[PDB]
Image (cartoon, rainbow, N blue to C red):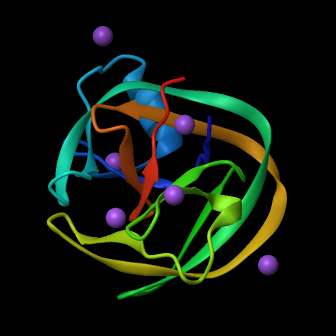
Amino acid sequence: GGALVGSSEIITRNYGKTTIKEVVEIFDNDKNIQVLAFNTHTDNIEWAPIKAAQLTRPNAELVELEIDTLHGVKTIRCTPDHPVYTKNRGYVRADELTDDDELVVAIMEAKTYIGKLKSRKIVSNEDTYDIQTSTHNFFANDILVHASEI
Ligand code: NA
Ligand code: NA
Ligand code: NA
Ligand code: NA
Ligand code: NA
Ligand code: NA
């Protein structure tokens, strides 16, 4: 389903912060990569093994989200259908988030804090990437997003 531009930052356990484009290249040979993610049951950050990583959607349509966070404005470019986790109503398509939704932001490898939508706009198409993880989610540019497998 949803996918991310290649410059979106992933927090890996063994390669440090890494763009998702570079993760896809590394995962072609190294199948042991874990990424910072989130257990929605216990509400705890967890490391999640990657099970797949690819350029899924070439020249895909995109929005750019600006998210107000504890540390200032974070931006993410993702397909309009990419789901973003909210604490108030579960996963929400990027193009359906509102300023009432409560996003989950990793402010360090072991703490989270609420994020709030600042703005959303269409941007020009790009090749997009995604990964599959054991938690069906991961942090992208410190924002908790969904990782589909179908
Ligand atoms: Na995806
Ligand atoms: Na890296
Ligand atoms: Na290998
Ligand atoms: Na909730
Ligand atoms: Na919902
Ligand atoms: Na707008």
Nearer to me, 14 or 120:
120
- Residue 26 drawn at (x, y percent): 39, 29
Name above or below for residue 4 compared with residue 44: above
Nearer to me, 96 or 79:
96
Ligand 3 lies in which image quarter?
Answer: top left
Name above or below for residue 57 compared with residue 108: above
Q: Quadrant of the C terminus?
A: top right
Q: Could you tell me which residue is drawn at 29 percent across and 20 percent down?
A: 31
Which quadrant of the structure image shows residue 120? bottom right
Q: Is residue 7 visible?
A: no
Q: Is residue 59 left or right of residue 106?
A: right
Q: Is residue 142 left or right of residue 37?
A: right
Q: Could you tell me which residue is drawn at 19 percent across and 63 percent down?
A: 109
Nearer to me, 150 or 13:
150
Q: How many marks?
A: 0
Q: Is residue 141 left or right of residue 77?
A: left
Which quadrant of the structure image shows residue 44? bottom left
- Residue 14 drawn at (x, y percent): 19, 41
- Residue 42 drawn at (x, y percent): 14, 55
Name above or below for residue 30 compared with residue 122: above
Q: Quadrant of the N terminus?
A: top right
Q: Is residue 115 left or right of residue 49?
A: right
Q: Is residue 3 visible?
A: yes
Q: Could you tell me which residue is drawn at 42 percent across and 36 percent down?
A: 23
Name above or below for residue 39 compared with residue 129: below
